[PDB]
Length: 415
Ligand SMILES: Nc1ncnc2c1ncn2[C@@H]1O[C@H](COP(=O)(O)OP(=O)(O)OP(=O)(O)O)[C@@H](O)[C@H]1O
Ligand SMILES: [Mg+2]
Ligand SMILES: [Mg+2]
Image: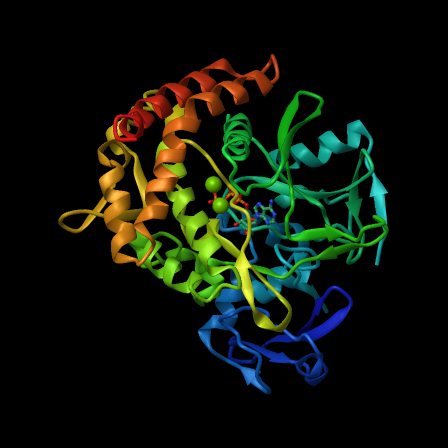
């Protein structure tokens, strides 16, 4: 049938699946006439009538977990009509990344430590996104291939939101990734990068990562929780999650930098994006694909980059399973004298400078970024280390700082 699409308390339009299986979307005239109307996606510009392009199917598919296995679980959990996005979202689309609420204001159930552990380990019983069969009003969806869930934090209590109430945190579970990401987010923050705050939460013998959502915002008085429109780069370019990597045809640095020229914060966003490329290289982050970058869609359809997220270093995984440093590749390659430069172990300042030059990113700014990491990295690693718990896995810290300092040496010798 039909899924009515809401942005907070406003009707945006409807998603329908035709008798031919095609996914179509139509904006409500009331939405189109609203003062600050904005599109669901920059790939789905405001217009009247049914939109039938592949961009519709892809946009909504990108709201679901990437893994075909996780999708199998959802189907089995809610006896979904099929595996298509419309049918899976009919079941779990009330709360997803961004502000799209799909249904065919503030209510919740507080969780006890015992119940919290139940949700956080439900995946062991083939439960998708911690949506235990016990509940029936816990419908959430979150993209990405890593096992996770999402919860509502009210004060210092964890809660399962009911109906259309939003979640406030994305909870990532162990597939040592929890400690890895925790460390990387702290290092990012220490270096002045825009990333969300996160904390390691405990529930029995379970250790998960609770990441504060930047697609959610409480009003000043903390009485109402709103969702903020947001989409990832696959969505913004109308592409399927299957091509998130540049090697599979997804957007690279050049395409995203050109797209950011249209940002309401273009110069800042371009600078921050290039800075983050140098950061990913330094920490051996190999999964900076298109779905790991997003933009907020603002009133009137303007857009701006969101904070960076899903930051994992490959360094702690080296050697243990035979992966060598020479095997680490940036998801989005840099310019090389000939072709591209992708090997973290072979990249130097010259590659960032050559890339900036061809992309019209000021050379002075690129030097600034490189020189800033050259003098700040040592102190940043130390400061983070001192901020880590005492039970934090020392091997993670060792693997990351030794490998970061090794690459950092390349910057300090130049700057
Ligand atoms: N703090 C946040 N606030 C808002 N949205 C977020 C936040 N962190 C992640 N997201 C969104 O949720 C998705 C899943 O998170 P994340 O990228 O961290 O997952 P993964 O690490 O599960 O992903 P992958 O599939 O690459 O392994 C992202 O693609 C992004 O759209
Ligand atoms: Mg991701
Ligand atoms: Mg990831």
